[PDB]
Structures are given as C-alpha cells and as structure tokens.
Image (cartoon, rainbow over all chains, first blue to last red; front, side, top):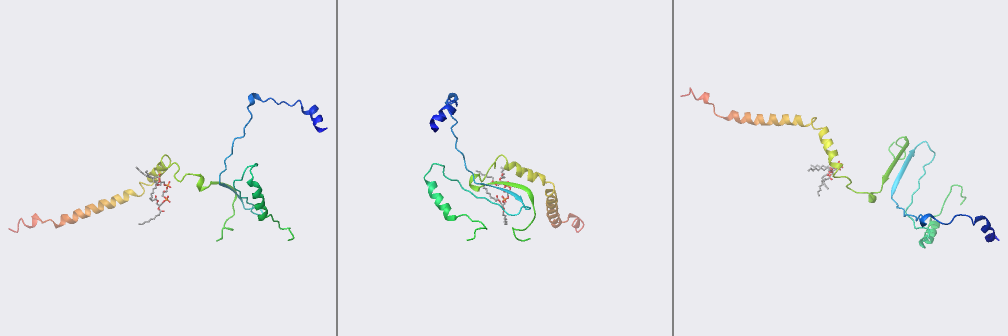
Length: 80
Length: 81
C-alpha cells in the first residue's frame, strides 16, 4: 500500500541531473589545533577533546563503541 | 595567586594554535625572518654603538700617548753637550 501510494505523490519529483554532475563528496582533512575562549565569569569550565575517527562505513567503529562503553559516562545525580 | 587555577580575571578573549606536527619549524626564515632581525638591529643601533666607539677612541689615544712618552727627548740632549 505504501509503495502504490508513493507512486501517485512522489513520481513527479525530478530525477534527471544536469550533465550528471553528481556532487561527489570531496574528502576532509583533520588538523590538531586548539581554541580557547576564556570567560572567567561563567560558572564551570567546559572542555571537549577529540581525535580523528573512522568513517561511517568501516568495521573498526564497532570495536570503538565497546571501548567507549568501558570508559563510561557519569553525572553527579547518579546514585551509584 | 601562585597557582594557574587562580591568577587573574580575564574575559572576552579567544586564542588559536596549531599542533607542532602540523607546521614547519622554520617558516618564512628567508623572506620574513631576516628583515625582522634587521629591523631589530637598526632600531637600537644609535642607542648603543656610538658610546663604545668613544671607548675605542679613548683606548687607542691612550696607548699612543703612553708609547709617545717613552720616546727619548731631543730637547733634553741638545744642551747636555
């Protein structure tokens, strides 16, 4: 039913692309830099640190997920 | 006052830096480095050099006068006869 319905309401969407100039995604570079916006009037310090990670379609990510779970999140309310 | 945690109170400032491994250790050391050194030297040349030149002049004259004194006196022997 869904497929038959989508035909009537989404068949008109254009599909022919100009000169087949599909916007292929260019790669992106990662740089080890730091930005420090200092404002001493704010309540708490607030930092974030990161490193280059695999793409969305690599097996390794699964293992990284496990490693993340080992580190674990935390909060002050947790009654542990 | 002696711990990085509490030294001063600053606000509304941002900073940007790059990793040591992402940049050259000698960037523009041929087109932008030398001229800056020349600026440094020129900007403080007349404030130092000339005084030490006076020292050199005082040093040379001194030595010259010292040796000039040890020369024999022809006016102390003209009449000695």
